[PDB]
Length: 167
Ligand SMILES: Cc1cc2c(=O)n(CCN3C(=O)c4ccccc4S3(=O)=O)nnc2s1
Image 1: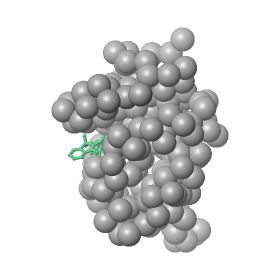
Image 2: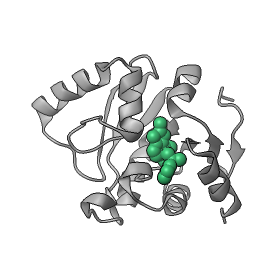
Image 3: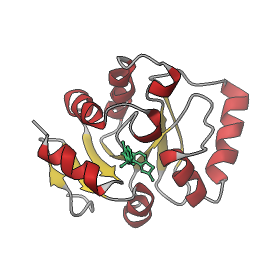
Image 4: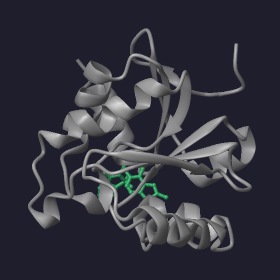
C-alpha cells in the first residue's frame, strides 16, 4: 500500500491520473519523481522547467555541478539526483526529442531506467514539448516498465484520450 490517490489502474503495474506532477510530488513526496530531462540537464520548460521552478532553482544548481563533473547524459539515459522539496530522489531521464530528430526507438531505452526503482511518479516520456505521440509513449511505458509507475498527465483532454484509447 502507498499514498498515491485517485489513479486509474491500467495494468498490473501502471496507474494514471490527470494531475500536475509538481503538485502530486509536493503532496505525496514520493521516493522517486521522474524528470523529463535533456542531456545537458538544462531545465528550461515543460515538466523540467516546472519541477525546477518548484525547487527555487536548486535542481538547476545541482544539475550544473553534475554536468561540470560528468558531462552530458546519453539520449535514453538517466541519472539520480536529489528530489529537493519534491521527493527523496529525482530520476532525470532523457527521452528522445522528436523536434531534434532523435530516434523514437530510444524511447524504450529511456523507460528501461524506471525498472531500477520499485515505485515512481512520472510523466509520459517524450510527451509535451519533446514532440512524440503520447498514446505511443503510454504504450511503450506499459510494455517496458515492470516496476510500479504512477503517471501524471497534465492535460485533461489528453488524459481522457489516453484512457479511452488504451488497449
Ligand atoms: C507540468 C507539466 C506536465 C507535462 C506533461 O504531463 N506532459 C506530457 C503530457 N502532455 C502532452 O503530451 C501534451 C501535448 C500537447 C499539449 C499538452 C500536453 S500535456 O498534457 O502536458 N508534457 N508536458 C508537461 S509540462
